Length: 180
Length: 180
Length: 180
Ligand SMILES: [Ca+2]
Ligand SMILES: [Cl-]
Image (cartoon, rainbow over all chains, first blue to last red; front, top):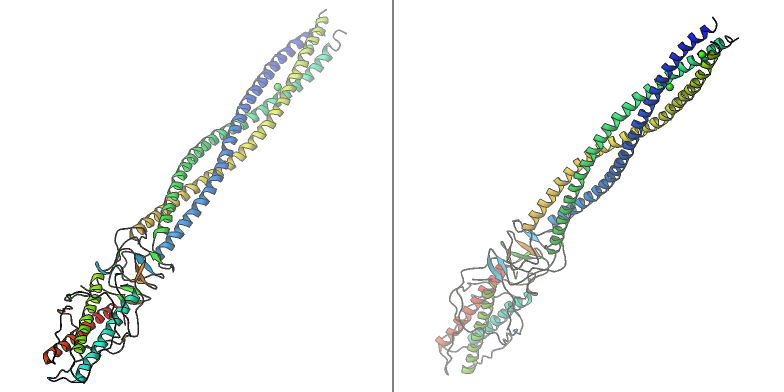
């Protein structure tokens, strides 16, 4: 019967409708689940990018700081190098020379013993013609048993020479500054 | 004609059911592809989170190290600065003054030439009253053809003056430390 | 009659098919929406990995740089320490000693006052026997009303002693280098 072949067909078609309904429902379920996982992933990505951006900016600053550090090191190393070559050392045994005059406080010492002190004052400067020429300290002066003008005159000359030689020595000390 | 399109609608309904079947399967396929891709994406996020966490911890330690570094830089710069102002320079042409006494080894030199050496020993100290007053080195002494007491006496006075002036010079050297 | 609810079953089945059609269509579109979001998410993950990989390598370089910095800091700190102990200070009040000879420019000074200058030239070296022995500066010389050989001779000896004492002093300055 044509109508009987309609309902048997209807029964088969509803079984198919049931199968489809379940399948569509499952697909919809999965999609909602996938969506949730996706939303969670998107959130973690946002936070990840926030952190990485912070790190990227932070590293940039670190490198800049490292540049300054390298520059400051270069600076202090440069000065130390300069100082090392320019400074007077207390343990070096080879002669050291200054390009300037020198001034110290109480005294100068050689080999632990004092050599030059402060300028000694209270002197009246001698006057005369300084004798820088030949000076014979072993010069002998003859004195006879009777008075001779030339002998005594020779004494006078030697005395005058001696006093002018003293002046020469004194002037030397004064020009150095050892005495006033 | 109840059997009609009861059967032809069944045909139409079956056509639509087959297409529905095809579409559901296609949707299922897509979901499966999405599921695989999402799972891969989620994993990479997990590893990313791990790496970023590591980077964050390493960077924090680095910043702490940089703090110590800046402090050490400040330290050495300060010290170099102190040294720069306090040290005696060998190339400076302007007069330099020490706050201390000074002791050197063999000798002191001026302009490459030795001026003061070690204290010279072996001296016997002269005795007397040093003459620090007026001393005329150009004093002339008259000697006549006949013996005159005042003339020879003046000679004696001049000699005594000279010798006491020598003592004054000698006293200066000993007080400085140039001789023992 | 059987055919009448054959058509009614068709009507009910049509509602279900229309519902299914919309539901499948909704799933399909939703999947396409997910794909777009997922593709965007994947892209950002790729860029994240690029940045993080860069940072990992960047951090490695930095730690290495930091090691060198500490090595350089130790070096300059050591050098400053060495320089600090070995250098001559302008502000130290305690006597400072050199293990070496010293040379300066124009002069040596004590307490702001010049003591030793450049070596004075133009001297002729005195000759004779230097008197380093006993020297009495307070020695008196008798001169009588009449010529006496021993008295005048004593004068001559006193003169010779003085001149030999001058020689001793001059020798001292010359040996030091204060004079040529
Ligand atoms: Ca049907
Ligand atoms: Cl579906």
